Amino acid sequence: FDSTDETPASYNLAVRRAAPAVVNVYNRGLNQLEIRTLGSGVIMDQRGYIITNKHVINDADQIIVALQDGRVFEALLVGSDSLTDLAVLKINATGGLPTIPINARRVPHIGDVVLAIGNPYNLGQTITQGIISATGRITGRQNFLQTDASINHGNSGGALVNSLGELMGINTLSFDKSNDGETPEGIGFAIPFQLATKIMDKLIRDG
Amino acid sequence: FDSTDETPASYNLAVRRAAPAVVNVYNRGLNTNSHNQLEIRTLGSGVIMDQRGYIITNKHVINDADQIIVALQDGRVFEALLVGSDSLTDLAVLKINATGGLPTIPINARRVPHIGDVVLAIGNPYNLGQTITQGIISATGRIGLNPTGRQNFLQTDASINHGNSGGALVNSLGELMGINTLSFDKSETPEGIGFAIPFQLATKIMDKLIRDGR
Amino acid sequence: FDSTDETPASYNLAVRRAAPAVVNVYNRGLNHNQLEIRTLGSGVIMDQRGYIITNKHVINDADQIIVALQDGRVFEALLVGSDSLTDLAVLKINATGGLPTIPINARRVPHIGDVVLAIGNPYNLGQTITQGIISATGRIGLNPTGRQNFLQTDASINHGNSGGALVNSLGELMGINTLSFDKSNDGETPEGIGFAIPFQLATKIMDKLIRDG
């Protein structure tokens, strides 16, 4: 057979659209100055506002944001919300920034293909693929999208997007509780994008 | 014109078709210590197979139950009766009595599962509530002797966890491929290796248990 | 609804095209006159002459290398050469009937997000197909792999997969599966992080081991 003109199944379109807006977040602390915790973040708009997780940036002497295009910025902590575990950062917007695609009218459905985008184990930006496993998941009263897109240490604060590259949520947690000394597989949680956007707005207002 | 109709890649169709028929199964035993109150000892999943209210699950999920509870995704909850079980295949059949119509799992008796088929695993891992995971059919059985000790397991890498047992593995059309039963969990932690009873064998065993109870 | 006429989404085409060329590799050793399996992995038949790519770690210190095809044929393989720098090894089998070979499209450029299937023999369960995507196609800066040209994938890779094939939805070879990531930060288990040698490099290193050693 000759598959030369056949086209490989791919979610590269979503990657080209969304990945440039997902950044590596470095929590640096005085050693000189070294990296304590690392995670990911999402550039939400041209103003330079970034969503990440609170646990990623906690007790940082200096927060660094690294874009996939090679630019590195010092980020300022705008605010954080312990109820939802989100935090907002702010970098220099001058020079133009890639932003995450957002479709405010898209309703996430169970079974939708999703890609997780982040920096696990500081390997560099990593794309993994799963589906929305459940919606409306939760002491705690939180609302999560559940996904089996592989999520690891470093993915926190990163993006979960669909095949169109639209933001579905912010990856936050990985289930690791074991009844029988066995390990959970493919159970991860993200803050739905609508909730995250709301929390970001409040935090920016400082209210 | 300003709002176009591009839609994300999705297996939601399979979910809408199959998921309503997959139930959360609760094995409950009475406790001598606290007022003879019923409490959960094991939990798993099950599949509603026909309108009469017959349900497939794993035998090890319902072993030694004082009370078996079945919860549907629409919010209905029923007490189920054990119709029978088969230890050779680890399958069990339950029966509920419902007034309204019951959702049933799509079954295409002529569909032949193929290695590489997209599948969804549907169940209630860790009692988080119904969960859908996605993988493919990794294998449709084995000719040679192997560590499973069996020759007819569907192997899949759709993530399966504690609580998924008794639940459904379906294709992208929502058609039943198998009943999720095992996970390879200890060796190095294995990843993406799970096993289901093929739907053909599960249907034959069910009919047998409904007819005889053995 | 009546789905009898609908077609299930499937990568079975890729499977039928690529899987027959992926073999089970057995590293046998003496421990008495009787030989025992010491290590097991996978391999990929690259051309009709019987040259097979595998991982060097799989075949190191072997007293006898055995290659099993999915069609039931079993051969003793000869170690043609190994390259420590890339952890690749080349084997050679001598066969009469004609051999299945892995599809290779030299002009295909792997892209991040591409659907891929890993094909190998994890835990000696038998040939296993798992599905993921290309998570990354190399690295620009220094990173924990120490290398700059790994394909990274979340297609589930397990012990026994090393030396096996990573192909796209068309059955075209993308890489040779080599590493899976198990380094934990604080007790957690890494999930869906695996690595493969890109097919272009694998081809080149094979050609050089064949003629030189």
Image (cartoon, coloured by chain):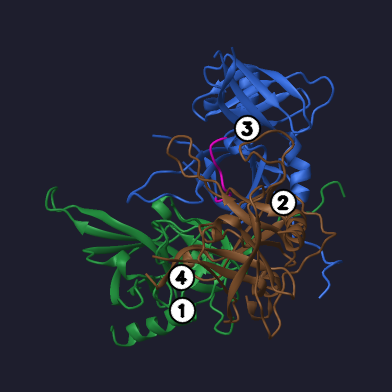
Chain colours: A blue, B green, C brown
The overriding secondary structure of the stretch rendered in magenta is loop
In the rendered view, would you say A109 is above or below B203? above
Res A46 seen here:
yes
- Magenta stretch? A148-154
Tell me the kind of residue under disc 4: Ala
Provide the residue designation for mark 3. A40
Provide the residue designation for mark 2. C113
Res B117 seen here:
no
Label 2 environment density (alpha carbons within 10 Å; few <14, some 14–19, many ≥20): many
Element assignment for label 2: loop
Element assignment for label 4: strand
- Residue drawn at the location 65% of the way across and 35% of the way down: C143
Label 1 environment density (alpha carbons within 10 Å; few <14, some 14–19, many ≥20): some
- Residue drawn at the location 56% of the way across and 56% of the way down: C156
In the rendered view, would you say A124 is above or below B209? above
Element assignment for label 3: strand
Q: CA distance from mark 2 to mark 3?
A: 19 Å
Provide the residue designation for mark 1. B152
Q: Which chain is mark 2 on?
A: C
Q: Can you say which quadrant of the picture contains the C terminus of chain B?
A: bottom left
What mark, if any, has residue B196 been given in the picture?
Answer: 4
Q: Which chain is mark 4 on?
A: B
